[PDB]
Length: 216
Length: 216
Image 1 (cartoon, each protein chain N blue to C red):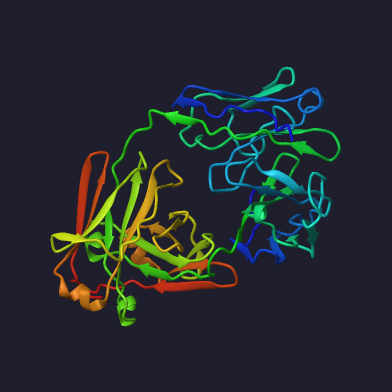
Image 2: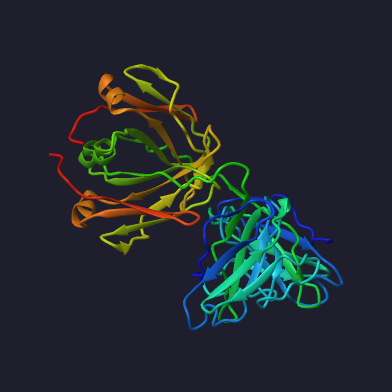
């Protein structure tokens, strides 16, 4: 219902400011002074970062900004944080206990430094065994470009079964995690000498080997 | 400034009626008599489905209904509709400078069987323990609507300082799984008595405990 209109993208680079518009109307946007800007870090709570026009709530930084001119409002983000990557929404009052919500934004700070994952393999759980199971997890974390890619290996040859592997996810910082998991029978654990969780990201390969050996 | 809580994932048959709750911290949370719900669709903008409590705003069909039995607000859907699939958010109202959005519910139309998680916790490997490293891993897998909540306790008290959870992914058999992780120092691991990974999902919540041990 004539959503307010927004820009489907808005790249910036650490320290650089940015500005997203939100085209409105004489009736939605230049009719009152009730434009809210919402965040949307992603797969989360919306979060309001500006209301009633140019009003920066309790605990947002000195750097978020809004100003409207005519039936157009806009959001400005000086010196780009690194977590400002999120989707951005405008919402305006439009008379009658009601509001309109012109779509997202999702900018991208760019020139984000790359990390390679901190692979961490994990042997099966005393408990798990005491249970007759055996899962091996391989946690991948603290990497940027969130296109990892992984393989298991049993004593130096592949294993193409019982291996679910999730998909990257942002993580409080601005690196992503992904766990790799492989399901085995206690017997199969003891049958082979080691298992390596082999992972390659942005060229780099990193392989961590775990052996049925310590306790558990 | 946070703290409005919602069931992770709520499921329905297609024709059935659902309910999503929203609770808080008292002398406002709900006491708050505002509380409006927002339906949010894949990559569409949150729209506003209910406001000021039980007040539908009118492009909106009448199955939507709202309420509060005190400290907790309720949104219920009647005659589940296919496009009723989505994420759903309760908004509460703060110091005029502070609109408060609760965690959002995922309504799914059950397209296969309901499956609660399988929670599996792994302590820190001796290796990691040697590298003056120390991480807990909480693997959560094989479950219906791909929504779950993750909480960690150190000796029974909540611990929220060093934790990352991976939104869930379809595995290769249509159920999902996610994992969370807590990174501490070995010291910090050797100090508590036990660590707990609690997972919540549709009527049930599993909690597992790991303890420290030399295993050597």
